[PDB]
Length: 395
Ligand SMILES: [Ca+2]
Image (cartoon, rainbow, N blue to C red; front, side, top):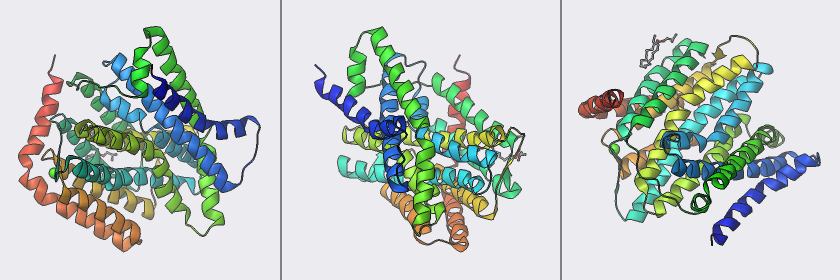
């Protein structure tokens, strides 16, 4: 049958239409409505992409690791942040700061809001006070630690060089490579992917290719209007543009990923749900950084480092600090209510109390909180090192 899921496909696909039709007829909307419509299209195309990636994963598991599907789940973030980086190199000006602000916003929101929210919902759903993670998480923990240690070298220099980007991309490439050699969990299907998997091979694969291309096309035809729409809306209002770039824009990019995470929690799949959020942190804290720095050179057609002013350096430091604390929490392969609430509070406090003083204070707290945990769980760091050591010598 699959009539219900066929209607779910058509319904959300149709959500791209208000913006796509507007593009087709070259109709100009005011700032806010342009943001809503183009944003509606981006979010919609994101679910399509996820539906497409999950079908391909069930189809050919060896080509689509859980890490890769976690990357494809946050494509709108790469496209929006990529747009800022493109403008930064081709035009310059405020877009230089926006590229880093958007990236740090995405990362901190993911942990501060995403990890905490999903954990809290899991608490009420399982009627418990602890979330346990798989042993395979030690992989992402290792790369998270290396990326974070490397990211601490960025506020010092005051920029992100082409070599830095090379490192971050290398870390992710190696991570992906090792994620293929790791024993994945059995991929369940439900909803749209289950209907797509029901179709004969060539029709199934043609369909998700069409979906990928259509959704990918939609995103690329939407991000500029959505990004400029946001910036415009914030300007005619009294709101600082940095708040829109850092907090509002990633919210629209990380929402589809969050919604899918919540869905899997209620279906009693907490482990896989957290695996994706943690792996998504990995790519956004590796590949994303490399991408914006690389794009900064490409759009300018010149070998160039992405500058980091006083503000953005503090943002990166704060983000690295939060990420250190995140790593230390994951070491026991469990997420408790204290740790989740700590992630939430320490995040929103910085957001509700702006200023250079608070950025340094919260940075210090993240780091100082991390050290006793890291010291008490030093065997877990060694274990994470051995996990990677085994994946290398698998064959
Ligand atoms: Ca923990």
